[PDB]
């Protein structure tokens, strides 16, 4: 049988980006673990998939992909329907706003939020490494300034790209989910339109399914 | 058909990403400078274009965009022809490789190459800031490992996504051009297929036109 394969730990943020997209479009898939403890990500077998030796990678027949956003867009295109059109590529202005807010995640929001996840969650929980409180403080101040902008945006529309959910919103889910596992989760409550947006995403069945994979089973 | 407008200094890397895409598709445009000396990027007029107060921004009628890659994709879609189709969105596997290598620029290549540009070129030439040789050395070692991967890829095809030029290749132009103005330019000679690809991009008429805009006096 023909499920597509995602390679990497299911709970890894960038894997969860891809599995969320797969769930949203109703595609059949399997997640194949990659064991970092044996350097499997640097094995020749995995380097054939991603020559830079990272996860996720992805296989659909003879096509091997890497870079979570590239994988995700392939999925969103391949399995597109009229009812689940998360890129909006037939409407140039809508597609442009999807792209803008996807880029805002990559270049503005995630660089502010991710260090807090690293320092407050990944460091202590993965290998028991310390937290750098200077990094956390600096990042929180940058994140507050980002959230001020998101608060204004999400007072004008229910989602980032307009009055429709899109890949832009989905891209914010994996790292933000882990931010909600840190002691700084309540920050979002100070930006009520951002909180309402987050709650809307968390209510989505595909998001619930992937959130359940981002915990300890 | 009034020309579309690109806002920012013409020689800025992320402005040049956009103007290269505009030249490749033969679109009429104007570059409108944004004066950082008077904080014009933080003025209400510019914040209406990019609420994060960065350049580039872009206007087409009533549409305002920011984030250079989002602007660029809007351009490549709007002005697409069968002859100049730089995203390949009608072919899932080709679009996927364009997307992979666009992501590799953003998340792998540019993070290794751009600090060398900053330390060796932008620091001394813009404000007269010092150079951090530790940053340069660490970045060079990362870049060498990246270039090994590019060398293998560019032995299989003349361009990153396949046997056709695409947005993936164009994304590498602006920072790489400035890297070639640093004392480390010769690094590429150690990767003959990467150097041959670079020379092919530099031979393109659109690339020549934008390279001429990328000067200080
Ligand atoms: N931009 C890429 C990031 C992948 C990545 O960082 N993967 C990490 C796991 S998370 O810190 C990884 O595989 N690292 C191993 C390494 O670099 O050796 C994407 O979105 O796919
Ligand atoms: N990912 C974005 C980066 C734009 C940017 O950094 N712009 C800088 C100029 S270059 O260092 C900028 O406008 N900075 C002003 C500021 O952040 O205050 C893009 O691709 O458009
Ligand atoms: Na849930
Ligand atoms: Na549930
Ligand atoms: Na929860
Ligand atoms: Na001007
Ligand atoms: Na595209
Ligand atoms: Na290859």
Image: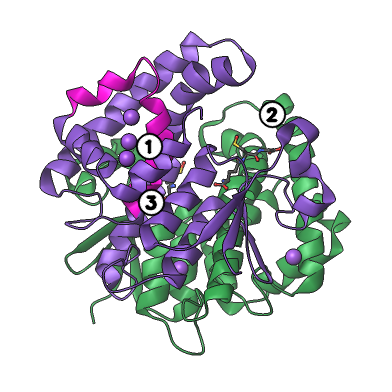
Chain colours: A purple, B green
**Mark 3 and mark 1: Cα distance apart in space:** 10 Å
Q: Is residue A172 visible?
A: no
- Which element is circle 3 on? helix
Magenta highlight on residue A169: yes
Quarter of the image that includes the N terminus of chain A? bottom right
Q: Position of residue A77 (x, y in %)?
A: 43, 70
Mark 3 to mark 2: distance in Å? 29 Å
Which circle, 3 or 2, is nearer the viewer?
A: 3
Residue visible at 12% across and 42% down?
Answer: A155
Q: Position of residue B37 (x, y in %)?
A: 34, 37
The answer as to whether the residues below labels 1 and 2 share one chain is: no
Q: Is residue A122 magenta?
A: no
Q: Which mark is residue B135?
A: 2
Cα separation between marks 1 and 2: 25 Å
Q: Which mark is residue A109?
A: 1
Residue beneath disc 3: A102
Number of marks drawn: 3
- Residue in the picture at 82% in, 66% down: B193
Question: Looking at the picture, how far across and down is residue A75, in whole percent?
Answer: 47, 64
Q: Residues within 10 Å of mark 1 (few under 14, many from 20)?
A: many
Question: Is label 1 or label 2 in front?
Answer: 1
Q: Read off the chain for label 1.
A: A
Asked whether mark 1 lies closer than 8 Å to ligand 2, one says no
Helix, strand, or loop for circle 1?
helix
Residue A37 seen in the figure: yes
Seen from this angle, which residue lies furthest left? Answer: A156
| Part of the protein shown in magenta | A168-191
Name the dominant secondary structure of the magenta segment: helix
From the viewer's side, name the closer residue of A72 and A26: A26
Q: Mark 2 CB in 8 Å range of ligand 2?
A: no
Q: Is residue A154 left or right of residue A29?
A: left
């Amino acid at each position: 049988m023909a499920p597509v394969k995602v390679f990497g730990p299911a709970m890894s943020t960038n894997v969860a980006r891809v599995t969320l997209c797969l769930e949203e479009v109703g595609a059949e898939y399997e997640v194949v673990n990659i064991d970092f403890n044996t350097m499997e990500h640097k094995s020749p077998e995995h380097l054939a998939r991603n020559p830079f030796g990272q996860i996720p990678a992805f296989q659909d027949g003879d096509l091997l992909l890497w870079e979570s956003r590239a994988i995700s867009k392939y999925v969103l295109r391949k399995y597109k329907t009229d009812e689940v059109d998360l890129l909006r590529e037939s409407n140039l202005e809508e597609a442009a706003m999807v792209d803008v807010w996807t880029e805002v995640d990559a270049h503005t929001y995630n660089p502010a939020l991710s260090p807090i996840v690293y320092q407050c969650l990944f460091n202590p929980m993965m290998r028991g490494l310390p937290t750098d409180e200077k990094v956390v403080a600096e990042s929180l101040e940058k994140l507050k300034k980002v959230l001020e902008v998101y608060e204004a945006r999400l007072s004008k529309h229910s989602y980032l790209a307009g009055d429709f959910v899109s890949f832009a919103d989905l891209n914010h889910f994996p790292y933000t989910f882990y931010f909600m596992a840190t002691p700084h989760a309540a920050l979002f409550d100070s930006y009520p339109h951002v909180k309402a947006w987050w709650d809307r995403l968390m209510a989505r069945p595909a998001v619930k399914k992937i959130a359940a994979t981002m915990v300890p089973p």
